[PDB]
Amino acid sequence: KIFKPEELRQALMPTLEALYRQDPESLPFRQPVDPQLLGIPDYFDIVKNPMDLSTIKRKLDTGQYQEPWQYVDDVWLMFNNAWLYNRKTSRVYKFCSKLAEVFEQEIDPVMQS
Ligand SMILES: Cc1noc(C)c1-c1ccc2c(c1)nc(CCc1ccccc1)n2CCN1CCOCC1
Image (tube, rainbow, N blue to C red; front, side):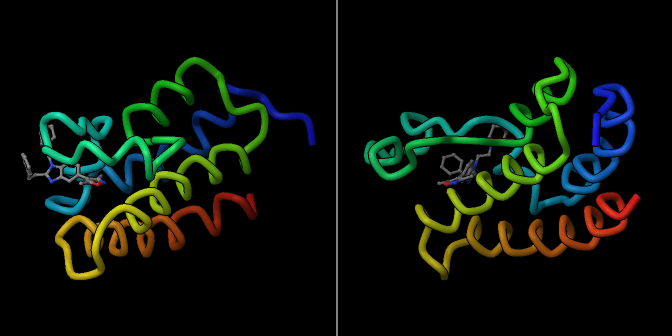
């Protein structure tokens, strides 16, 4: 499959928008994790490949995703990072799990079409 980056933007962006609409659950994911602001100086040791919603949006706007799985891989990276770093009892871990449930529902049909 050859992929049109504006046709992929139009197909994929509503799945990203689905994640942004979740409030409060998307709030920690809207900008890059800032370890200084959050007081978590080991974050970049543990999380080698950070990702967040703003980064995925800018990637999709600059035509960075040659094919849709690369996009799906970034969304999962963002989730896996938050699950790796955070305790299971934490607000952000539980928000991650909600976002992942939303994403799975949204992306399923879109990757079909
Ligand atoms: C994502 C992710 N992965 O690991 C952590 C830790 C986060 C993360 C990532 C971000 C998190 C956050 C947790 N909790 C909050 C709000 C509470 C807070 C805690 C300490 C200091 C200040 C606030 N935010 C901050 C959310 N703000 C909202 C407004 O825009 C900037 C980020």
